[PDB]
Image (cartoon, rainbow, N blue to C red; front, side):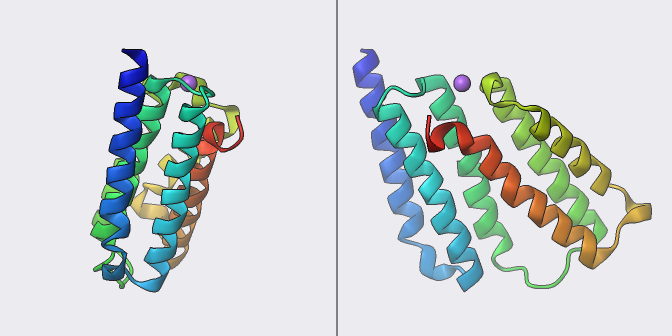
Length: 157
Ligand code: NA
């Protein structure tokens, strides 16, 4: 049923949230805080979907997107130094792919400001203008807020 597939996804998301919260002690203090924020977004997806304020395709697309960002948090948790440009460029490209995949699956989520932010993210991926400290801070800023903007449809629909 549509109602059974709905209960299936809510069950998946709850098991997913438990798995990662149960590992939060592996994370640095800062990364724990990022995990709490991402799990709040997962809660927003569940409640919006429970209340039929989003459909299953969109909810699952947002879940997939956050799944990737949560795993990247664990990936980065053993990194404290500034990234090489090679590592940085990989990170920017990967995040852009996750954005594009999400918008392909949930095209109602795009906005002018998300499109503009994609372009500013692309411009960071440029070795000639790369400033190891500033470029990384700017990437992390754009990434934090872009995740918030892409998930905003589930916050108070
Ligand atoms: Na949608």
